Image 1 (cartoon, rainbow, N blue to C red):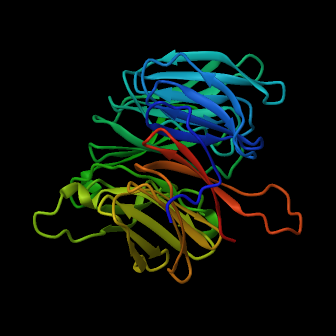
Image 2: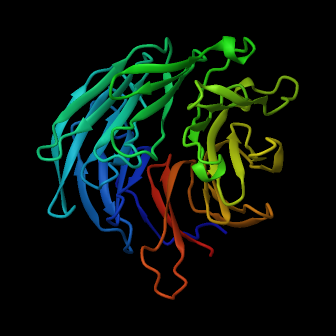
Length: 379
């Protein structure tokens, strides 16, 4: 009950803000407040160090590999984006190109299914989508859009279901607007304003695409999430029609307004559930047909990330633990302990091949203390 981790990586000298994993190689990338990115392996004790990435003007806040496994894309708070090219079957990562089109990047993300593609949003509200040349790793801009009038807090690709050439992105802003884009043309498909949500002010924070298996084939249903407790579930394939809208919490007197902030959203197709996690530490599991809460968990402190995986819900917390819940029962099974300060992000890894052996999943964290921890978790 103090540290049940398997191993760790602690080369960062400041907060570990982002963590990404290669789609096929046992390779982690973490980005930190020391303006560095470190590569290390996820299959050994202790991790093997695989290199340090340099060139940033600020803290690194995004690390993600492209879906096909070529290229690492990293972003920092001075607005720089760097592209490293995988060489020697992922054994060496060479800087291929870089850019700096904005003052500060909030969020990046590499498209889950279309090769060599990524998008990012900035504090000035702008939205950018790029592709990466397969041969030399050069940058190819698809679009640049300036519609949001405050910070572009999050983006999420949609219709990821339809092959290359169907490249669509939903972005949201603290100015209450939500926009969908055709990334290839830079065309704004629809834009949600206060007018569409009863005139409510709703500075958006979180976005999450629903699995098609839960929406009867619709590959464009997105749950949103504001910093004052507003949940909107929108149909991006029907002009952003609102499928659900509610305030998810009734705050207590003089309780923090940001306590209602929806920090993370995750869907479960298996259980027809959508979980949201709040700054006040509440975790709410919604039935995705009736949009009513099914289970409610309450953590000691702020939820920082939620992730459904098989029968479980994983939840990282700013108290420095990662909790694992039985998605069906609601029972706490297992808590990852050993961090001093908060867990800012995490990934979950499965054993690649079925060996007729049990083989546990791994949670690997991004710690505010500058430490990543590797946990083996039940079933």
